[PDB]
Image: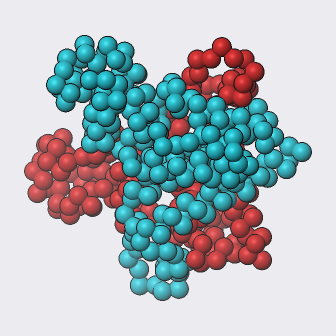
Chain colours: A red, B cyan
Amino acid sequence: LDRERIAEAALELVDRDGDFRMPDLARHLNVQVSSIYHHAKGRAAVVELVRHRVVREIDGSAFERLPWDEAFSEWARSYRAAFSRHPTAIRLLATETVRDPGSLSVYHSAAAGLRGAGFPDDHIMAVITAAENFLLGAALDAAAPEVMIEADSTTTDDALTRALAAAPRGPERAEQAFELGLAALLAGFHHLLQECG
Amino acid sequence: LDRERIAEAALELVDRDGDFRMPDLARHLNVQVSSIYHHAKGRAAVVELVRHRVVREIDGSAFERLPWDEAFSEWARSYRAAFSRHPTAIRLLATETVRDPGSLSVYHSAAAGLRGAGFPDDHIMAVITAAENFLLGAALDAAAPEVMIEADSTTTDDALTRALAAAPRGPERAEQAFELGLAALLAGFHHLLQECG
């Protein structure tokens, strides 16, 4: 029983149900809640351990090594991949305040990278949050069925039929939308930067 | 007991737990599963009724009345507002194939609007899905706490501290990120269109 084993069991419960309760977590660790509190004080601390375990693969330090848009793209891909492994954890983690030191570090890196690029301070958090909104959505879409829209029509030339026939099939469907949306957002952010001088 | 009352009770369960089970739904309607199946055959049909009840407010027909980017903005705002009332339903609805006639109609409208604008057919579904990815994420962020990042630092001039101090407070935090991300995506999509001639 250390922090890593608590984080593990908690994420397992969150994977199954979308949330966890302290006594049930203790049961699955064969301990009393007491024992958990010695490693992590309260629910908020256990949520941050869950967050830590999900986001471990996300490297923010790419912002120190690459131009902002290339770093943004590496960071975005890692973020998608991390959350797409735990789609049932997305609601919980998107709606609890971030305090995990590891996560705060990633934020520190993205903020410094975007400042370095010329994004004004009053825009930096919105840029990062706009990107995260898209990425949590794309993580859900990567966990979704490969066919997400099934239309029952007799028409062959309407716009929806045509668009659905001309789109990628399989895992490529979600990948196409993710790549196009990422490129569109980066183009938008580049525009923001031109406007700022 | 009609389709509307089934849709209602099912969404109530989904709001609470993130999913529903047929027998529990029947219990909360004081009926046997049998009675549900006469209005909606199986789980997939009940999921689409849930979808219908969430997305009723979303008007796709704005694509018939406004230039694509103005329509996109009205549609996006309605979509955010709808899902932000039921954040616990987002996972389920983002990961089940769309067959609800009302929803398919909205897709029909957005597809025709984007075709009308000049987006090539092989790009239309990805454009719509990219937008939805962002919007589901923004719906979660609107249901999130107004302070989403709490940093414990002694530093005053670092990039994260500065960005968090210069950002909007309260409900304005999520609103700022939503507005900036929407504008960035539309700029990106406008760029896509310039590239296409």
Give the vertical position of A57 relative to A175 (above or below): below
Q: Is residue A134 left or right of residue B23?
A: right
Q: Is residue A51 left or right of residue B71?
A: left
Between B196 and A179, the residue placed more toward the observer is B196
Q: Position of residue B162 (x, y in %)?
A: 53, 81
Q: Position of residue B38 (x, y in %)?
A: 32, 13
Give the vertical position of B44 relative to B142 (above or below): above
Q: Position of residue A196 (x, y in %)?
A: 73, 75
Between B71 and B160, the residue placed more toward the observer is B71
Q: Quadrant of residue B196?
A: top right
Give the vertical position of B126 relative to B75 (above or below): above
Which corner quadrant holds the N terminus of chain B? top left
In this view, the residue farthest toward the right is B197
Give the vertical position of B193 relative to A119 (above or below): above
Residue drawn at (38%, 77%), measured in percent from left and top?
A: B152
Which corner quadrant holds the C terminus of chain B? top right
Q: From this viewpoint, is residue B128 visible?
A: no
Q: How many marks?
A: 0
In this view, the residue farthest toward the front is B65
Q: Position of residue B144 (x, y in %)?
A: 39, 59
Residue drawn at (54%, 36%), measured in percent from left and top?
A: A142
Q: Quadrant of residue A152?
A: top right
Between B65 and B10, the residue placed more toward the observer is B65
Residue drawn at (79%, 52%), measured in percent from left and top?
A: B191
Between B86 and A133, the residue placed more toward the observer is B86
Q: From this viewpoint, is residue A119 visible?
A: yes
Residue drawn at (34%, 29%), measured in percent from left and top?
A: B4
